[PDB]
Image 1 (tube, helix red, strand yellow):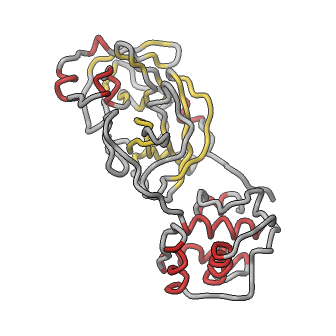
Image 2 (tube, one colour):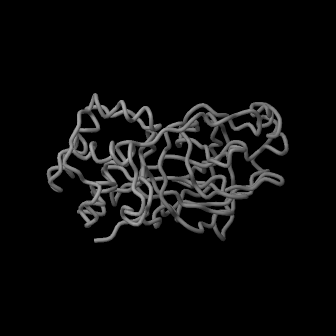
Length: 301
């Protein structure tokens, strides 16, 4: 039974977390083979609080200035580099734990587990979802910068997301492991904003099926509705519109729970237009747009 916030184990990744330092800035690093990735702004001081020139800030730095404390032992930074917003480092020893891996650039709505760390040492791990306007509602703090996101399939860790900034709006922004920021944004403590945010319609619907496979069936109703028709109520409620593509993905939980998707859309369409007033859903008392189809299948298979 049961259902809740569930992240992947962090074993393989914990073995790839290191410490990296530069003057008075020191942030978490991901150490795969012999390379050590980490946010490029690590070389910035209050220089970030303006318009730091990375090219220049960089070229004006050398290896010896990088304190890479891989846990308890300190390696020798044989070199550096720069791949977009990421700072690629090449060191003497290759990591003897480096697990089979890939670098993936997830899409909004997708979910992943994030291993929060401070000075190379992880502390906790939770789940997150690439929100519409490309942000992430995580729990990062002074030094968390460098923490990663990922998913698993035993055998293979697919790295998506590295933490860089926290917008003055309190939300979080980062990149894939190629130094590319998700959504616009820049590693500048300047100017920046977080456009209006939508709700991950599919995730909500997937969660509902979840809430169904585990009792709770009050929200389900007889009235049904259409895809071109539902989308209309979705605009009123900063919801993401529903493609036929999402309908095809819910297909599976649908056939197994015994509830046609467009039907599930009629319940939500209602939930939104009407409300709840007491009757909750799977603990929550709000729609959980933070569980993807596949995420719901994991806990129910």
